[PDB]
Length: 341
Ligand code: NI
Image 1 (spheres, rainbow, N blue to C red):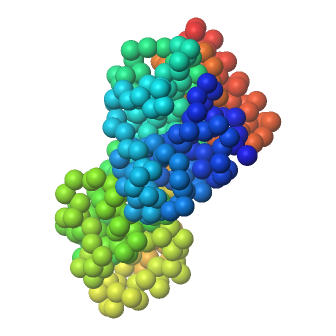
Image 2: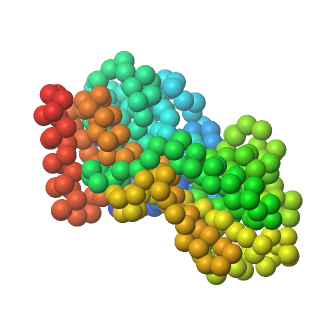
Image 3: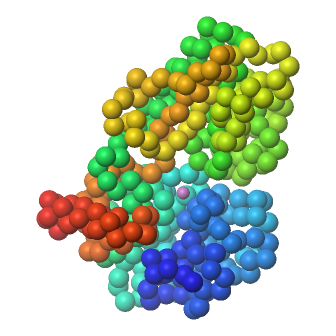
């Protein structure tokens, strides 16, 4: 049964609410982005109108084989009427296709649901800037001040420089990169660009990536593993054993592996700088774990809520415990007192 923080009050609308079967009183189901926690339940036997972005729609048609008559793609930064109500889609600065949604309720109330997001000062010059938000449904994944990480550009900087140095020192090494889902494609697209290579990958990852409207993409990725010195692998293979095993498949082409595990936040960030990050190494194989976040840090989150000045905030991540809720409400009150709204 559908939780309260996935219902839009005063409408026939739900948000990322697909795993509960037939939601009583729902006429238009919304999907913020193509990640498994959010789409769980969708398939070729889904028969209600789904609203989403274009890219999200491609992933529904091609990866879940949801039928074409039910996918309603909506363009961004655009006022659209759905079941008598004005919606707007804005960039979530998360993974590809990821949106936030602005709902204009018939009784004058105005709701922002954030989906998943990495807050950015650029969001302060979107269509949000024109007006007031009475309720905010907020991705609170890193809502505690100990959650610090670098900017995406610092992380990619470090990944480029690392990879170009190792391969200029050893022209016979292979670079591998981890993935489970969509998102973080810059990790491997930038490493492959500094290095002269296309990216090598499986048939399933290649077709996921063919859904994402990335320009010049046919020139960047391939299913021919042998032609490539950057390779994509499932995240669970980025371990000494998984790699050893992959190094054998390549057949005396490479004699060294440098691997990148993109993680979210991890405790080591509290003490060490991006600059100072060091690998695990066994013999001829090395693994870097890198804090490439697609979620707001604490500092980013707070800044966005203070510019937005909502009347009421409802969290959507970390909702399960009394101690987590209590913690999050304490930061909402400090933010509000400080900015004075
Ligand atoms: Ni997500």
